[PDB]
Every structure is written in structure tokens, then in C-alpha cells.
Image (cartoon, rainbow, N blue to C red):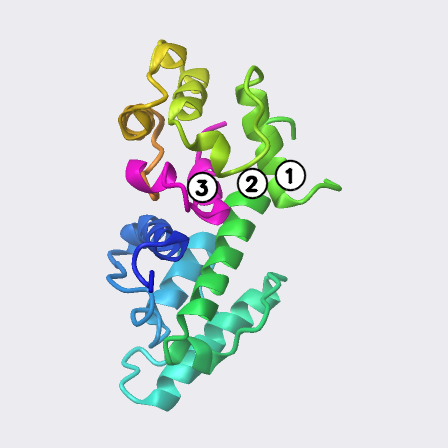
């Protein structure tokens, strides 16, 4: 009966914004993740931007027929396999036919690989991408216990700590912030990061402090922090 705005919607929203931040640079955009990858073209474009390589296989530039759309998605999935990016439970018809569950899974694989796992973090790897992101954020704010990507972020004040850590003076009074004003706190921190640290708001202040936020969404946002 709550098929409206859970962690599930936050995650679709966040994964869509992340894709769109990348698609911007080739003049494309997704309105609806369930439908707008289904002909393969926006998926191919996203993969080319993330990898900085073109497709080596031909594909259908006007995929008006189902078979053309299946083949475009196959070209994209095959490209990822070649890049040794590990996919699970995904085939071409899953994308073409709008299996939202499996589409979200694919986009998470891309985020984990290109945003979390591939960049060389602060201190230059037997630990998972998640552990590495936690440690990286923990080191920027050594006076707060950073052990998750949900409850630690709920009062909006750790965002202020992280942003000010990156450029002292952006959120200097973060510790004095009212923990009962979480959207206010998150909004200020995240707008400072947007305006001055180049961090896009792929999750929103309302979303990031929501009691039902999923960790993947928060990780997607936090993985963008500089240096």
C-alpha cells in the first residue's frame, strides 16, 4: 500500500540524476529510467561517456523495431563484459521491456564501477568499493563515527562537516546547527558543495535525510566529493 516514494523511488530518482549528469555532455537526458534506456541509444551514449571509448560494434541509429532495440542493448551489455564489468541477472529483453528492478541493478553496477571502484582515492585494495568509500569519508571527518550511508546522515550535520572539511569556511558552524532542522542543514551543506565544490545534487536534501533512504543513493552522491 506504500507503492509511492519509498527508498525505491529515492533510488530511481538518484540513479536517474546520476545518469543525467553524465548524459549532459552529449546533449541527452532521461525522463523515465523505466522506458528511456529501452531502445539502447541512451544506454550506449552513457557507456561511451563513462568509459571515454566509442562502441566498437555497429548498432541501429533508428531502432524503431523491437529486434533493433534488443540488439542495441546487447551491444551495450557486451561492451561492459569486454570492460570486465561484472553484471548479474541482466539480459537485453529486461532493458527493452522495462524491467525496472533489473534496470536499477544495471545502473548501480555502473555507479559502483565508474564512480566508486575505479577512481584512485586519497590514500592511493583488499577492501570492497563500499569499505573504501566509507574510509575515504571517515578520514575527511575524523571526529564523527562514519559507519553507514543512512542513519549517520539523517540530521544533516555530517554533510556540513564533510563540506567544510573539503574547503574550511564553507560550513564553518556545522556543529552548532540544530539537529532538529535536518532538511535545512542538508540543503545548506549540499548547496555549498554544488556551488563551490562542483558536487551535483543527484540526491536532494529531502531525500538524503528521509528515514527510508537506501545506502546506494547516499553512496552515489557521496562518491562525487572531490580529492
Q: Name the residue under label 3.
A: 218
Residue 168 in sight in this render: no
Kindly identify the residue that appears in the image at 26 percent across and 26 percent down: 184
Q: Where is residue 72 in the image (x, y as percent from the top left)?
A: 41, 78
Query: Which of the marked residues, 3 or 1, is nearer the chain's N terminus?
Result: 1
Q: Confirm whether the magenta stretch covers residue 207.
A: yes
Q: Mark 1 points at which residue?
A: 131
Between the residue at mark 1 and the residue at mark 2, the CA separation in whole angstroms equals: 14 Å
Left or right of residue 19: residue 89: right
Between 59 and 197, the residue placed more toward the observer is 197
Between the residue at mark 3 and the residue at mark 2, the CA separation in whole angstroms equals: 18 Å
In this rendering, the answer to whether 157 lies above or below 216 is above
Examine the image and state in which quarter residue 89 appears: bottom right
Q: Name the residue under label 2.
A: 119
Kindly identify the residue that appears in the image at 33 percent across and 60 percent down: 2
Examine the image and state in which quarter residue 209 appears: top left
Mark 3 near mark 2, Cβ–Cβ under 8 Å?
Answer: no
Query: Which of the marked residues, 3 or 2, is nearer the chain's N terminus?
Result: 2
Which SS class for mark 1? helix
Query: Which of the marked residues, 1 or 2, is nearer the chain's N terminus?
Result: 2
Which SS class for mark 3? helix
Q: Confirm whether the magenta stretch covers residue 3.
A: no
The stretch of residues the image draws in magenta is 205-227
Examine the image and state in which quarter residue 171 appears: top left
Residue 225 in sight in this render: yes
Amino acid at each position: 500500500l506504500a507503492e509511492d516514494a519509498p527508498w525505491k523511488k529515492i533510488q530511481q530518482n538518484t540513479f536517474t540524476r546520476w545518469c543525467n549528469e553524465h548524459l549532459k555532455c552529449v546533449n541527452k537526458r532521461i525522463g523515465n529510467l523505466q522506458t528511456d534506456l529501452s531502445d539502447g541509444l541512451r544506454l550506449i551514449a552513457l557507456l561511451e561517456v563513462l568509459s571515454q571509448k566509442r562502441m566498437y560494434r555497429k548498432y541501429h541509429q533508428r531502432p524503431t523495431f523491437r529486434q533493433m532495440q534488443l540488439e542495441n542493448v546487447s551491444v551495450a551489455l557486451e561492451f561492459l563484459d569486454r570492460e570486465s564489468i561484472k553484471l548479474v541477472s541482466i539480459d537485453s529483453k529486461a532493458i527493452v521491456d522495462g524491467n525496472l528492478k533489473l534496470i536499477l541493478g544495471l545502473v548501480w553496477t555502473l555507479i559502483l564501477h565508474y564512480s566508486i571502484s575505479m577512481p584512485v582515492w586519497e590514500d592511493e585494495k583488499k577492501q570492497t568499493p563500499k569499505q573504501r568509500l566509507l574510509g575515504r569519508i571517515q578520514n575527511k571527518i575524523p571526529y564523527l563515527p562514519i559507519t553507514n550511508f543512512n542513519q549517520n546522515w539523517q540530521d544533516g550535520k555530517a554533510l556540513g562537516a564533510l563540506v567544510d572539511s573539503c574547503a574550511p569556511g564553507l560550513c564553518p558552524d556545522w556543529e552548532s546547527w540544530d539537529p532538529q532542522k535536518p532538511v535545512d542543514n542538508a540543503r545548506e551543506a549540499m548547496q555549498q558543495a554544488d556551488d563551490w565544490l562542483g558536487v551535483p545534487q543527484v540526491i536532494t536534501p529531502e531525500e538524503i535525510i528521509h528515514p527510508d533512504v537506501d545506502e546506494h543513493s547516499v553512496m552515489t552522491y557521496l562518491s562525487q566529493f572531490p580529492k
